[PDB]
Amino acid sequence: THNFARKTFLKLAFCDICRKFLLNGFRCQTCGYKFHEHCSTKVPTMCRQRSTSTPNVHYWEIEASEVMLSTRIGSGSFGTVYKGKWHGDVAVKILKVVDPTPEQFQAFRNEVAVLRKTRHVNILLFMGYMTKDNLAIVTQWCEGSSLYKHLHVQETKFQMFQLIDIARQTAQGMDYLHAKNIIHRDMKSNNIFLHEGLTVKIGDFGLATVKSRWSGSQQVEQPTGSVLWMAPEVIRMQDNNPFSFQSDVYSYGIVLYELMTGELPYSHINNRDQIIFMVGRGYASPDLSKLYKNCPKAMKRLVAECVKKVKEERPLFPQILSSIELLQHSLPKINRSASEPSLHRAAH
Amino acid sequence: DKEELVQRAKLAEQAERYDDMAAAMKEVTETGVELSNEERNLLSVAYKNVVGARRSSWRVISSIEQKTEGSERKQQMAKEYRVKVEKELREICYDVLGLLDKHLIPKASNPESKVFYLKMKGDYYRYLAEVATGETRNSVVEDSQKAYQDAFEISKAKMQPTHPIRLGLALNFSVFYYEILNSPDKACQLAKQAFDDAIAELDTLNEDSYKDSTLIMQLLRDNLTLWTS
Amino acid sequence: DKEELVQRAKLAEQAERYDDMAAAMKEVTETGVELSNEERNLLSVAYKNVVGARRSSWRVISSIEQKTEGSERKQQMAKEYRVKVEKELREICYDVLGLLDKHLIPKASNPESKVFYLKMKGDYYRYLAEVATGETRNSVVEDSQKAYQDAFEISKAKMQPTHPIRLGLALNFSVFYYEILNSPDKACQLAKQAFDDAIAELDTLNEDSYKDSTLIMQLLRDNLTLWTS
Amino acid sequence: ELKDDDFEKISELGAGNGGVVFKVSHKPSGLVMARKLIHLEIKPAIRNQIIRELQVLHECNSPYIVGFYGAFYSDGEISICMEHMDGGSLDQVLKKAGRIPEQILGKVSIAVIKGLTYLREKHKIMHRDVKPSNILVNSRGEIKLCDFGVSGQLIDAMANAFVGTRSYMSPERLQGTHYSVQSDIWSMGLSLVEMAVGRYPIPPPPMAIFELLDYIVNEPPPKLPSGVFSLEFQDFVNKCLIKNPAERADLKQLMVHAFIKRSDAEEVDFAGWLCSTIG
Ligand SMILES: Nc1ncnc2c1ncn2[C@@H]1O[C@H](COP(=O)(O)OP(=O)(O)OP(O)(O)=S)[C@@H](O)[C@H]1O
Ligand SMILES: Nc1ncnc2c1ncn2[C@@H]1O[C@H](COP(=O)(O)OP(=O)(O)OP(O)(O)=S)[C@@H](O)[C@H]1O
Ligand SMILES: O=C(NOCCO)c1ccc2cncn2c1Nc1ccc(I)cc1F
Ligand SMILES: [Zn+2]
Ligand SMILES: [Zn+2]
C-alpha cells in the first residue's frame, strides 16, 4: 500500500528506519513513511553515503517558614500537593519519606540542583526544596486544570488541531528534558497541565531518589507510579536501571493514545495487578482502533511507534517532534476530501 | 525524437523538477502522435504535480488569510499574493484544457483513453472551480459537470466497474459533487454505488492492476467514512 | 515598505514556494541595509532550499549518467541535462555570492554575522566546487578553503564552542575536507576537536537554542562514524 | 445522611495503596466510625453511579461482614463510612506477633469462609480483595470482612492505581481467564499461608512485583514448612493453593472440610490472647 515516490525533504526530516537525518529519500504519499535510499534494503514496508552538512535552522533551598500551606489539593504516588503563596502562587509537595537516609539526602540534593538548572517554556519551574516540613519540594503552580482532568472528569471538548499542538508542546518539553540528560520517570496526564487554557506544562519530572524508596544506603530499584503509562521494560525490572529515554517515549505514547482516543488504555481490564502482568509479558497493548476517525494516519503511526514493545524501536523525542511539526504543516493540505492519488510511481 | 522527449520527461521526473517534465510532455503531445499508456500517464502525473504544488500553496495562503478577517493591512498583501498564485494556476490549467480540446480528446481511438481524457478535463475544470468565484465559478463548474457526465456515460458503456481508472473517475466525480456542487447525499450515493458495483465482482483483477485498484477502493472507503453524515 | 517583502518571503516560505522567497529576499538585501537575525536566516534558508533542489537534481542526473553504461545517445542527453542543471546551479551560486560579498560580508559589524556570511560563502564555493571539475575547480576550492579558514579563526576567537554557527561551520569545513580535498585524516581531526570542545561545555545549552546545537552534535557524531570506517 | 464537615479525625487507623482510613465521630448518634478516604478522579455521573452502587451495601449486614453507614463524595475522594473496628486488621497483629497460632488461624479462616459464602449466596457480590489487611478482628473476638467489590464502576475507576509491592491474586486472574469465587478462595489460602509463616512466602525458605507475578504464575504454589503445623491445616493450605480452579475446591467443600470442622469444634479464648498481643 506504500505509495513510495522520490522526495527531497527540504524541512527537518528524519528517516523512519535508521532514525537519523534524512534529506534525500522516498516518501509515501498516503501516510508519510520516509526513508533513505540506502535504508531501502533494511525497510520493512508495512502500510556511497555522502557526509551530512548543516541543516536549515528556523537561594540554594527554601525555608519552610517563608511559605504558607493552603487547603490541600490532592494526593499522589509519592507526595501530597498543597497550595502555596511563596513569592506568588506555588505548589508544595510533601514527599512521603519521613526519615531520609543521609546518602539518599545527598543524592536528592544533587538531583534538585540538576532540576533547578533547567528552565523552559513547556515545563513547570522547579524553585527548590524544604527540609523543615519533612522532605518537600516546590514547583510552579498551574491554575489551569490537568490534562487528565480535562480529558475525563471535565471532558473539555478539543478540536483536533488543538490536540495536535498539545502533543507538539509536550514533545517539545520532553525533548528539552532529554537534552539536559534528564529521564522524566513517572510521566502521565496527571503531570501535564493545560496552563492558560492551551499551553502544555510538564511537571513532576526526575526525582528518582525520592519516588523510589531506599532500603538504607542503597536504592531499592523498584517501580513506582501509575501502571497505565509505565513502560514494559521498567515494569519487568529485569535490569537495575531500565529508566531511560525510551521509557519516557513509551509513557508519552500512552499519553498520545489517550489523547487521540479520549479514554485510558486497557479500559476493558479493571485491576492493577492484571494490568501489570499483561503489560510486563506483552499480552496487553493500547489498542489503536479506539483512535478518533478523523485522526491523521501520521498520528496513528507515531502513537504506534511510541508504544513499541521493544525498547530500541521507540523513536527518540527529536524524531517525534520533527514528525509532529511535519504533520502540523501537512494539516492545511489534507483537511478536506481526498481524490485519486499518484499511481505506483515507485522506483526499483 | 518522441522517445528522446519521453526519456527526458522521465529524467526530469526523477530529478524532482516537474516544470521541465510538463513542458517536455506538452510538446510531446503537440506533435500529434498517438499517445500510449505510459506517455499519457506521465503527462497526467507531470501536470498533476505541477498543478498540485500551486494548489497546496493556494490552500495554505487561503488558510493563513482566513485566520482573522478583522485584521490589519497585511491581509491585503496576502489576498494579492493569493490572486497572483491563482493567476499562476488558472493559466497552467487552461494550457492543459486547451491541449485536451485540441489534441488529446479529438484523436482518442480507445474508449479507455476517451474516458481518461474526459476525467482529466473534468478534473482540471474542477481545479479551476475552487479558484473561481461568482458567476465564473458557475460557468467553470458547468464545464466540469458536463465533462464528468460524458466520462461517466462512456465508463458505464465500455469499461468494467472494477477498472482502476473507472474507480478513480467515480471517486473524483463524488469529490466534485460535495466539494463544489454541495451535494453530500448524491456524492455519498455515487461513492456507495461505485463501491458495491466494484466489490460485487472481485478476484478478477489483473496482476498489474492489483495495487492501484485496491488503493482506489481504500481511498473510496476513507471518503465515504469521512462524509458518512 | 521593506517589511512587506519580508513577510511576503515568509508567506512564500510557509507556502513551500521558495523561488519567490529567494527573489523577495534578494530584493530585500538589495536595499543596502543591514539584515536582522530573522531576515538573514530567512535569506540563508531560502537560498539553501533553492540550491538544495538543484543539488539533489544534479546528484540524481549524475547517478543515472553513471548508471546507464551503454552505447547510445541516452548518455549524451543525460549529460546535456546535467550541464543544463549545472549552469543553472552556477547561476544561483554566483547570484548568492554576489549578494554575499557586495551587501553582506562587507557590511557585517557583529562578528557572528561575519562567521555566518563567511560560512555561507565557503558553502556556496564548495557547491560550485563539487559541480565544476578542471582548472576552474582549483580556484573555487581555494576560495572555499580561504572563506572556511576566515570563518574558523573568528569562530575560534569570539564564538562559544556550543554555538550552532560554530558547530555548523566545523561540520561544513570537515565535509569540505573529506569530500573536496579527499583527506579523511585532517577532516576527522577537525571534527573530533569540534565535538570534544562541544562536549566540554555541554551544560551551556539554553532554552532559546538547544535543539539545533544537539542536532549538529549528532550529525558530527554520524560523520565521525562514517569517516572512521 | 453523611457530610464531610460532620466528621473530625482522632488518629490514623491504617494506610495503603487505596487510601487512608481515619477514626471519626458521628454527632447525631455518638459512635466512633472508620471513614475510608480513597482518592479518585472520575466523571460526576460516574460519582453518582458509584454512590448508587455503594448504596446496595445497606442491606449487606451479617455477623461476619462489616456493616455500612453511608458513602459520599466530598472533594475528589469517595469517603466510605464503615463500622469502626478496634482490633484493626490482621496485618497489624502480624506486625506485632511473630506468627498467628493455628487455632486463631482456623478461626479467621472459618469466619472468612462463612462471610464470603453469605455474600455469594445472598448478594452475589464479588470480594476480589481477600487480603490479610482487608480482614479485621475485634477485641471481643468478632471477625468480619471488609472492602469487597459491590460497585463494579468503583473497580473500573480504581484500575488506574499505582504499582504495589506484594500481590494476593490467583494465577487465573492475572492471566485474564475466567475468575469466580474460586479466585477469592485462592486469595484466602494465600493469605492464610502469609499468616502461618513469618514472612511473605512467595520465595519459600528483594523481588520485583512483576517477578512475584511470574513466580505465582509459572511456578508451583508455595507450601508451609512441615513439622510445626497440623496435617489438617497442611491439607487445607494445599487444597486452597491449587493453580487450576477446577481441582481447587469450592465453598461447599470448604464448609465440610475436616480442618474447618475441627477448628469449629474447639473453643479458644483468643479474645484475651489478642488483647494481650495488641495492648
Ligand atoms: N503545579 C501544580 N499546580 C496546580 N495543581 C497541581 C500542581 N501539581 C499538582 N497539582 C494537583 O495536585 C494533584 C496531584 O497530586 P500529585 O501528588 O502531584 O499526584 P500526581 O498528579 O498523580 O503526580 P505524582 O505525584 O508525580 S504520581 C492534582 O489535583 C493536581 O491538579
Ligand atoms: N474499619 C477499620 N478499622 C480499623 N482499621 C481499618 C479499618 N478499615 C481499614 N483499616 C485500616 O486501613 C487500611 C486500609 O487499607 P486497605 O484498603 O483495607 O487494604 P490495603 O492495605 O490498602 O491493600 P492495598 O493492596 O495496599 S490497596 C487497612 O489495611 C487497615 O490497616
Ligand atoms: O475499598 C475497597 N477495597 O479496598 C482496597 C483499596 O481500598 C473497595 C474496592 C471495591 C469496591 C466496590 N464497591 C466498594 N468497594 C471498596 N470499598 C468498600 C467496600 C465494601 C465495604 I463494607 C466498605 C468499603 F469501603
Ligand atoms: Zn505508507
Ligand atoms: Zn535512514
Image (spheres, coloured by chain):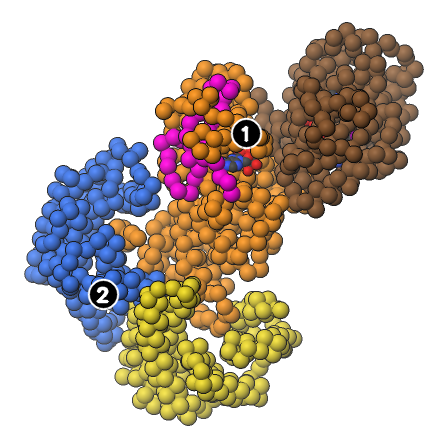
Chain colours: A orange, B yellow, C blue, D brown
Q: Which residues are magenta?
A: A115-144
The C terminus of chain B appears in which quarter of the rendering? bottom right
- Residue at image x 67%, y 37%? D158
- Residue at image x 37%, y 75%? B51
Q: Which residue is more in the foreground, A288 or D257? A: A288
Q: Which residue is mark 2?
A: C1
- Residue at image x 64%, y 33%? D39
Badge 2 amino acid:
Asp
Q: Which residue is more in the foreground, C72 or A236? A: A236
Q: Quadrant of residue D19?
A: top right
Q: For mark 1, name the chain.
A: A
User: Measured along the vertical axis of the image, is residue C138 above or below residue A242?
Assistant: below
Q: Which residue is mark 1?
A: A70
User: Measured along the vertical axis of the image, is residue A86 above or below residue A195?
Assistant: above
Indicate the position of residue B216 as horizontal and vertical percent values.
53, 71
Note whether residue C20 is visible: yes
The N terminus of chain B appears in which quarter of the rendering? bottom left
Q: Quadrant of residue C86?
A: bottom left
Q: Is residue B18 left or right of residue B69?
A: left
- Residue at image x 75%, y 22%? D25
Q: Is residue B154 left or right of residue C76?
A: right
Q: For mark 2, name the chain.
A: C
Q: What is the magenta segment's predominant secondary structure?
A: loop
Note whether residue C229 is visible: no
Indicate the position of residue D267 as horizontal and vertical percent values.
90, 11
- Residues packed near mark 1 inside 10 Å, few (<14), some (14 to 19) or many (20 plus): few
Label 1 or label 2, whichever lies nearer to me, is: 1
Is A300 magenta? The answer is: no
Q: Secondary structure at mark 1?
A: strand
